[PDB]
Image (cartoon, rainbow over all chains, first blue to last red; front, side, top):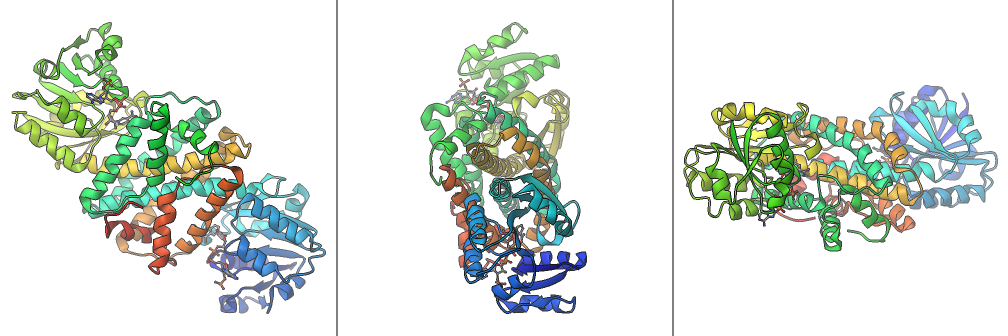
Length: 288
Length: 287
Ligand SMILES: NC(=O)c1ccc[n+]([C@@H]2O[C@H](COP(=O)([O-])OP(=O)(O)OC[C@H]3O[C@@H](n4cnc5c(N)ncnc54)[C@H](OP(=O)(O)O)[C@@H]3O)[C@@H](O)[C@H]2O)c1
Ligand SMILES: NC(=O)c1ccc[n+]([C@@H]2O[C@H](COP(=O)([O-])OP(=O)(O)OC[C@H]3O[C@@H](n4cnc5c(N)ncnc54)[C@H](OP(=O)(O)O)[C@@H]3O)[C@@H](O)[C@H]2O)c1
């Protein structure tokens, strides 16, 4: 029954709380909306009135808030972190991880590790469900056992910023997948198809796309841009998705993809593979 | 078995090589005739014109860039009497109906539309699925020939269906690529190995793949309540932009940020990803 504090009782915060409770720990919680602790009071959880009193209560602080900005606001009056390990499970950018690591260090925190939970709340605590962890190996190692309450942790690096870097990279893929999937479902739906039957038909094709991704990552690393699926042809197919959508009276996502491919053609990269879009991104700070 | 092919691009040349490998008597036409050079050794006949290529065989395969190029290339093909047309040219549902009409008007026996769902290098593998729509009988007749490009799947008697499902599947592919390109740009600029990243990512991408049928049920059942609201997802998309700015790396997923923003405005911030589908079905708009 080690003492753990948890800041944030949102969708993911509350799933974290339940995992930590089941693990057999003595849990102090704080949330802006204290009512979100209501389902935890019966399970023997203490609700601290302020972030400060919450952090005082335990040597191990878990944070799972909306964002860095909300994390900075919440930690504002948390003056004393002596002998505390911070486990930050708040989505943010690599520098935001470094910024919170710095905020808690300046306040006497013993250590900081950052975690990206890669599943929705309902999956938290399945050994299958993976959380990526970055920060000092000894710090991970001391929290490993507690952290096993939320599923399998993968320590990806000693660098505090890395779990967030990989988080942002993986959420990029997820964002792209959902954008395409939502566009796919709007088209088949409006045209009077059953979305569940379409999904059964799509799943084998979506698995093939997943299997082509490593080959593409190799192409990117080796700057090998020639294949049988040029950007000119792919752009023509995206334009037909727009027209297909228009024909049905449905809206059109993938605009950034259309824009970056349109410009790619302009710069005489029209004959390159999808791997050729990566240098379009790495060489220019722009929102397509 | 006499087959005519119109189009010797990346996919057209792969089709040609499948049809040769399966013992067709191939006649070809392409705007750039030189693209038939690898086929002349193998005994293929090059026709001077679309008309003379179509004239040469009972069964016509078309694999051109677009509908526009197809109608422009069929401009002086005025006699399809006796011809069965297999159109493997990507296009809209309405374009498939237009070519079917265009080719009927000129005397074609029948017309089927197919959508090849693999790159040329995988064409001819039984694992490679080409969606076919059109008359069952017309498909039944061509099924044997088409076995050369892999496994064909007759999705509907309705000519427009292969192109409907094609556009739907290519939407997913374009999203997946958009995401992957963003991910690779981010981790590459950060000094990570793209191939080691891909190994790490693989389990996670397969997991996303598995989530999609559930989301389809949510869309059909109009069930938009879960533990992953759009406000939370938008916040994460915004962090991908800032992560990218930190690295001096460009950012895609613009239409995804935009539609989620409007969702939040319309009071749908609490909804799941499934709550985006009605944002699209309601309004003709580019996001
Ligand atoms: N599917 C998921 O839910 C999921 C999956 C993986 C990772 N994550 C990550 O987990 C983190 C939390 O996500 P969530 O799903 O728990 O989101 P959520 O349901 O929106 O909860 C957000 C949390 O942030 C707090 N908050 C927001 N604005 C605040 C403010 N201005 N001042 C103080 N507190 C504020 C909320 O307090 P109130 O309760 O008072 O609103 C709540 O505790 C995010 O960074 C997210 O990306 C989530
Ligand atoms: N490549 C793939 O991975 C892939 C996968 C699945 C489906 N497809 C679909 O298959 C079709 C063929 O794609 P592809 O990869 O063969 O594209 P491609 O390599 O761009 O070839 C385009 C073909 O259309 C011809 N063409 C273009 N503009 C023309 C014009 N104005 N007049 C006459 N002919 C013209 C080209 O002639 P020239 O040779 O003279 O330029 C060439 O034969 C497309 O609809 C595509 O979406 C492709």
